[PDB]
Length: 288
Ligand SMILES: CC(=O)Nc1ccc(-c2ccnc(Nc3ccc(N4CCOCC4)cc3)n2)cc1
Image 1 (cartoon, rainbow, N blue to C red):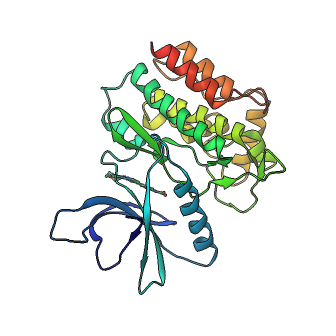
Image 2: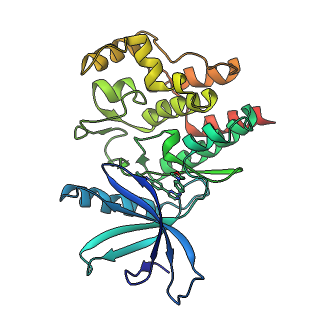
């Protein structure tokens, strides 16, 4: 199957809701009775013209991706008399890695964190070969199939690199996850493979903090900057902080070797940052 029908595909559960739209658990039942495959359906809320243009680009990006650590594309569903667009993805039962690590839990140590770390790296290597820049790497955007496998999701902010340059300038945003952003992504709005490496360093940081309330990237940066400051002054302070080796501290219980990987990812020099292939091999060699 590649095209999913509106008359079938029955609602089961609401998975996620935000300003972008809503992702919902559904069962595609063509026969149908009750025996059918469970799939995740993504739609839009507060929809305009530009959001459909970006959503259609998001579908095409996800369609071109076929990897064990990337959320699988199933198809598309045209609803409301073929006047609305919906993305069909596979369903992963254990939700986001952010919720999975906070609640499943005192069962994950460094070597299991590195297993998830390695899988994120391998998925990012696949995205590099297709010249895609994720731009939104976070533990909340990584989905969990089972205790042994995690998959990269949320490709809404993913941009395709031009044939001319190795970077992509994005001016549109307005609201952006600035605490995962690279210095050049903040100052010059430049996004590349190396900016994803920077963001991955923050993802690796999130994992070894076990997402404890006070140890989160936004909470730690605002502690160094001053949690009393609001609007742009946060960004001005963050830029000056990152320019002069201001970094997220080593998590409680995190080995020195792992924090070295974080700091290497957090390099102000763009070209000095390690590739995702270098990271995946280093992480796997530490595992055994
Ligand atoms: C912005 C965006 O792209 N969001 C998003 C959210 C999701 C998924 C997705 C894809 C495949 N499977 C799942 N499964 C899943 C199952 C349970 C939860 N939760 C468990 C209960 O608590 C709420 C979340 C979340 C996701 N989600 C894809 C794109």
